[PDB]
Image (cartoon, rainbow, N blue to C red):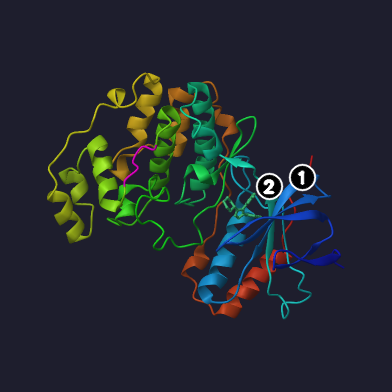
């Protein structure tokens, strides 16, 4: 029973993976865990194998590990990261302590593309279209990415995009400080935690991304939280009475009102020489009031993606049960919960 494993010390990290994976070669490591590039002899794909660090060292980590396995096991879309395999050398639940995850190796992200300069309108419709397609699928399952930025969109030679590095796990702490790109794409309402966020925060991120693809420049590259909010409000206008009442923090409201009111700028004078349809879409995505922002499913129907929009080919996801988020379990219960999901994984078909 079970495949044969083989262990090899890699840059001070013992990797014990099934032999179907060959030519393992370090490609990065961090707070997520260690990632290795390898050749998967069964699917014929070059893959990325992630060996989580201390997967069950705490209940926060035990839950994190579980939340990511559950999410990766659900995501089944072309434009979204997916699980090709999950395994543990552990013979029994008693010795289960390591979790390795496998997905298609991604080479370049959107970043190793835009930086060059501004992009062609066609490639902008395509890339953004794909982002919105994955998103309509992600949100239809009540999932919020929370961290949509260029570095989190894997892009290939034929401009095919996949959304990865979801939030559902890590908690941004002290990483959003200063002149950092980790924050240039967050909606203002989640950036200063004015209110509890909705999935439209993701739609705000896409507008930021789309704007950058068009101009070739970061839309709101603020040097700190306040400076960035200033950049946003200068373009979108200051909150109105309708919005102000939706902000719980009395301090936030008090701060906001201390600012000299400003009208929404003319997007056609910001994105000079850009397709009127692109401009029209940004105006709909970049709305201060998250309640009035366009939805992924609606964006797709927008005349900007006429060339690619196919209603019958923009699938939604199966219902996604994240009731466990409310569950209070001990380290060992998230651990056993993680084990069953590993144990029960079913590979996606082939070609
Ligand atoms: N090189 C590469 N290619 C594909 C994915 C990743 C990956 C995974 C990951 C996820 C699921 C899985 F099953 C296996 C690995 N977790 C983080 N990253 C990187 C994503 C880009 N920035 C640094 C970390 N890295």
Dominant secondary structure of the residues highlighted in magenta in the image: loop
Question: Where residue 133 sits in the image (x, y, percent)?
Answer: 53, 37
Residue 65 in view of the camera: yes
Q: Residue at x 38, y 46 (%)?
A: 184
Quarter assignment of residue 156: top right
Q: CA distance from mark 2 to mark 1?
A: 8 Å
Q: Nearer the viewer, residue 346 or 209?
A: 209
Q: Residue furthest front?
A: 11
Do callouts 2 and 1 mark residues in contact (Cβ within 8 Å)? Answer: yes
Q: Residue at x 57, y 46 (%)?
A: 317
User: Which quarter of the figure is the C terminus placed in?
Assistant: top right
Q: Is residue 313 above or below residue 253?
A: above
Q: Is residue 219 magenta?
A: yes
Q: Which region shows up in magenta?
A: 218-222
Tell me if the residue at label 2 has its CB under 8 Å from ligand 1.
yes
User: Which quarter of the figure is the N terminus placed in?
Assistant: bottom right
Pick whichever of labels 2 and 1 is earlier in the sequence. Answer: 1
Q: Quickly name the residue at label 1.
A: 45
Query: Which mark identifies residue 105?
Result: 2
Secondary structure under the numbered disc 1 in the rendered image? strand
Q: Is residue 266 above or below residue 2?
A: above
Packing grade of label 2 (10 A; few <14, some 14-19, many >=20) is some
Q: Is residue 108 above or below residue 170?
A: above
Question: Where residue 297 sits in the image (x, y, percent)?
Answer: 46, 36
Question: Where residue 8 sits in the image (x, y, percent)?
Answer: 79, 66
Quarter assignment of residue 86: bottom right
Q: Residue at x 23, y 54 (%)?
A: 247
């Amino acid at each position: 029973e079970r495949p044969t494993f083989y262990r090899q010390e890699l840059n001070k990290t013992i990797w014990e993976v099934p032999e179907r994976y060959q030519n393992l070669s370090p490609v990065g490591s961090g707070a997520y865990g260690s990632v290795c590039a390898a050749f998967d002899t069964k699917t014929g794909l070059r893959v990325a194998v992630k060996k989580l660090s201390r997967p069950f060292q705490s209940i926060i980590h035990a839950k994190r590990t579980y939340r990511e396995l559950r999410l990766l096991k659900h995501m089944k879309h072309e434009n979204v990261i997916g699980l090709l395999d999950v395994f543990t050398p552990a013979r029994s639940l008693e010795e289960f302590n390591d979790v390795y995850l496998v997905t298609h190796l991604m080479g370049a992200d959107l970043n190793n593309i835009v930086k060059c300069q501004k992009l062609t309108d066609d490639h902008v419709q395509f890339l953004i279209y794909q982002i919105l397609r994955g998103l309509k699928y992600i949100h239809s399952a009540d999932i919020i990415h929370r961290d949509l930025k260029p570095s989190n969109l894997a892009v290939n030679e034929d401009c095919e995009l996949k959304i990865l590095d979801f939030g559902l796990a890590r908690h941004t702490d002290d990483e959003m400080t200063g002149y950092v790109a980790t924050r240039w794409y967050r909606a203002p309402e989640i950036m200063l935690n004015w209110m509890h966020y909705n999935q439209t925060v993701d739609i705000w991120s896409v507008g930021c991304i789309m704007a950058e693809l068009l101009t070739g420049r970061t839309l709101f590259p603020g040097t700190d939280h306040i400076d960035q909010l200033k950049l946003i409000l200068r373009l979108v206008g200051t909150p109105g009475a309708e919005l102000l009442k939706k902000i719980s923090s009395e301090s936030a409201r008090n701060y906001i009102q201390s600012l000299t009111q400003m009208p929404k700028m003319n997007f056609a004078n910001v994105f000079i020489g850009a397709n009127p349809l692109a401009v029209d879409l940004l105006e709909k995505m970049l709305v201060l009031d998250s309640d009035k922002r366009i939805t992924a499913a609606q964006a797709l129907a927008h005349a900007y993606f006429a060339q690619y929009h196919d209603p019958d080919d923009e699938p939604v996801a199966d219902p996604y049960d994240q009731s466990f988020e409310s569950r209070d379990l001990l380290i060992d219960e998230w651990k056993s919960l993680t084990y069953d999901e590993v144990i029960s994984f079913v590979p996606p078909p082939l070609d």
